[PDB]
Image 1 (cartoon, rainbow over the protein chains, first blue to last red):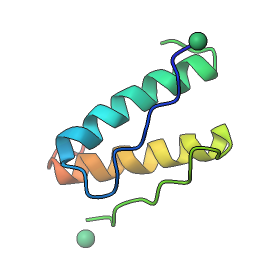
Image 2: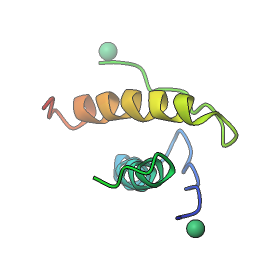
Image 3: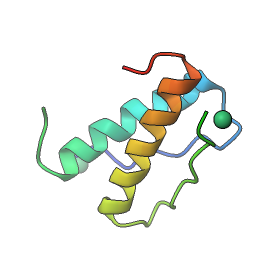
Length: 36
Length: 36
Ligand SMILES: [Zn+2]
Ligand SMILES: [Zn+2]
């Protein structure tokens, strides 16, 4: 599956936290075998 | 709004990454003024 996303840091702009959130969602969906 | 969640670390168990994901979602919804 996808490799584990890198956390962009506490001080990242909101746009980058949103990007990380989306990548983390995808990662967790694959790890849990639930790609919906 | 809620304070910014603390990242639990790359090596956290999946359950804790899910918990962080949910807390981050709530945080981002409030920051973007879109609590749906
Ligand atoms: Zn892979
Ligand atoms: Zn507050």
